[PDB]
Amino acid sequence: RKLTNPVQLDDFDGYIKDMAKDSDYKFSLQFEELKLIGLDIPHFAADLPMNRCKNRYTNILPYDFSRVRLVSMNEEEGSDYINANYIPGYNSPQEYIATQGPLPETRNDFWKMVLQQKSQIIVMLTQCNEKRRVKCDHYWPFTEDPIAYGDITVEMLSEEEHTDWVYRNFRISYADEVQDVMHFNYTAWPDHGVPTANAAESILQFVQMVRQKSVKSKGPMIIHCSAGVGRTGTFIALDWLLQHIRDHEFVDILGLVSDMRSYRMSMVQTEEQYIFIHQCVQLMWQKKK
Amino acid sequence: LKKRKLTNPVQLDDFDGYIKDMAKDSDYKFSLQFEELKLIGLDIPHFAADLPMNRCKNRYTNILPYDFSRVRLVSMNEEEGSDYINANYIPGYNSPQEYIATQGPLPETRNDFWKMVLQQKSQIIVMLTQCNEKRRVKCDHYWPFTEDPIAYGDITVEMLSEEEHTDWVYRNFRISYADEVQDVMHFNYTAWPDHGVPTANAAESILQFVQMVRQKSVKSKGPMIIHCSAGVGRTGTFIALDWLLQHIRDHEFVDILGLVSDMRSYRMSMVQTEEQYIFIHQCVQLMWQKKKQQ
């Protein structure tokens, strides 16, 4: 089916309450359907034998149509491959790019994609390691002296670390093409599960922050986490909603997530993140002051 | 829903036996493959093509381009569909986006066509339809009638030489914008009826035409723009024939099913009829040529 369920913001408070009744009954009903969306969309380039070492998780693959293909002077197989997908935005198509966390083996491909797409913004929603589990390579420089990742060099002009997130100003270049890239790393993600922390504002400050800097990245805003679908998806939804609530008096979270999954699988992976989005949609309380 | 990657590479020496088997039981297998080919890309977005103002730019309401592979016009216009044109990049035997598959230009998307031609640096155009077939409108005569330069919006086109042949015609145009100048060859095959195929008598004809366009392929910077009416059936069988000409040359096998299945994921209806899908196989007995020359 085609998922959609617009709700007037004036009734959103009652709505989510009615969604949680009977042990999140309605919620799991909608989410369970979200799990079906896009289950039969080809991702043949992802299945290719020599691309397997480029897919972090054997089961989180990019659809063929929405995949961000790299530009190489031909040859080989899967030479244009990177586990990434364009995701529609509130302002235009291919507004975002949802990728998995780069691997020691797809590290150079990542920076190649940042340049070829002219993405001047990267949002990282996970730490390299969490609870003694590898989640993402540290694909960027550890210091200020430039590191050459393939043909693209990377120079971290500055590294600003805060309490919940971290900012980095990189300056990558190829041949005679210098390009700036801002990097925001949310490190205090609410575990992922739960949630709680009335301070869901912390994620909202982060979103607002990235958002108020989007007016600089001609290319897509590259967002990623580990698999690039669970937290990545929640983020994108929030960056959408933030704007959509600002300009409308209704929100269709179901449609939103449904939209996103048609472009990349598992976008917003758990019923917890999906309910968390509604918890955050209390952005209405604020739109009332 | 579809979930299997269609493909069936057949060794050229077993082609006679393979096409024989595909023809058994009144083309039983040719249908099995074709019916599944028809499922491809059915669930691929094409919103740009549905925008209110792009509707008049679509020759047919049921033949639209997929968002991911569509060709975009560049311009300052900040209005709806300003970058739109019913066209898709189609992978190549040589490179992705080696061709551009479009519908025949409409009187109202004509200027858009030439813009694409210059912006993509397409120096070759393959038109597989007559502007009119049996009193039915198939494609606008979007190009000049005389050697007199004609301004199509911001691009003037001057027809340099016109050569009307048996089953086809050749034309060399020089288009320009400001100082930017570009030569473009135009190959019009007029013996391919819409929704159909050349006659059994034009079998050699069309293959010679593909040969002629293949020799020139190299002289073009951008993708070869090939088009017909809806830009999918005749345009799809051509792109396939061009591939196979090259592949058959350097290889010992063909995978027509994978080829067509491939094209169809970049633009809908590529190789529209089962008859055209089979025509391709008959043509693949291009091995005849191979086995001879050498």
Image (cartoon, coloured by chain):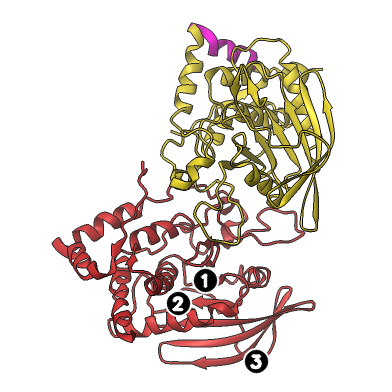
Chain colours: A yellow, B red
Q: Is A84 in front, or is B293?
A: B293
Looking at the image, can residue B58 be seen? no
Q: Is B188 situated left or right of A275 in this image?
A: left
Q: Chain of mark 2?
A: B
The answer to the question of whether label 3 and label 1 lie on touching residues, with beta carbons closer than 8 A, is no
Q: Is A268 in front, or is B285?
A: B285
Residue that label 1 marks = B104
Same chain, labels 2 and 1: yes
Q: Residues within 10 Å of mark 3 (few under 14, many from 20)?
A: few
Amino acid type shown at disc 2 = Thr
Where the C terminus of chain B falls, by quadrant?
bottom left
Check the image and name the residue furthest to the top: A22
Q: Which mark is residue B147?
A: 3
Measuring from the top left, give residue A270's x and y in whole percent: 53, 21
Measuring from the top left, give residue B290's x and y in whole percent: 33, 80
Residue B208 lies, with reference to residue B34, above or below; the image says below
Q: Is A74 in front, or is A208?
A: A74
Q: Residues within 10 Å of mark 2 (few under 14, many from 20)?
A: many
Q: Which residues are magenta?
A: A12-22
Q: Which mark is residue A229?
A: none
The answer to the question of whether label 2 and label 3 lie on touching residues, with beta carbons closer than 8 A, is no
Amino acid type shown at disc 1 = Gly
Residue that label 2 marks = B129
Amino acid type shown at disc 3 = Glu
Real-space Cα distance between discs 2 and 1? 8 Å
Measuring from the top left, give residue B72's x and y in whole percent: 64, 59
Measuring from the top left, give residue B67's x and y in whole percent: 56, 52
Q: Earlier in the sequence, mark 3 or mark 1?
A: 1
Q: Chain of mark 3?
A: B
The answer to the question of whether label 2 and label 1 lie on touching residues, with beta carbons closer than 8 A, is yes
Q: Is B195 situated left or right of A50 in this image?
A: left
Looking at the image, can residue A70 be seen? yes
